[PDB]
Image (cartoon, rainbow, N blue to C red; front, side, top):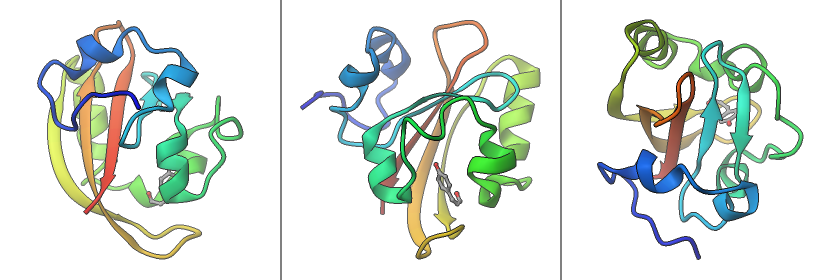
Length: 125
Ligand SMILES: *C(=O)/C=C\c1ccc(O)cc1
């Protein structure tokens, strides 16, 4: 497995070297979102929670079509503020209920080492 703990401070440095496959060995959900909310990466872990297909939701809008349940001031609002601000590192509990059993999860959002890329790590709680 890809040994890298959830919530690690230097996670974007460690993760900035993993291809898709490399990214599928993680013990938690990982999503790469561009500046507009377009899915750049989607690993198998999150798929296992949301039931979506990693290869299927690539290139689609996450807040608009993939995960509308995150279209709120509590998810989206924080994201845009971060996008616009140029930075963001925030941890929070949340519930994904769209097209699925309500699953009490925890979300960690942080800007990547790259320019306009943002990470959205998720785990069961
Ligand atoms: C709220 O988040 C509902 C559904 C959902 C859809 C896609 C992904 O990746 C997570 C959760």
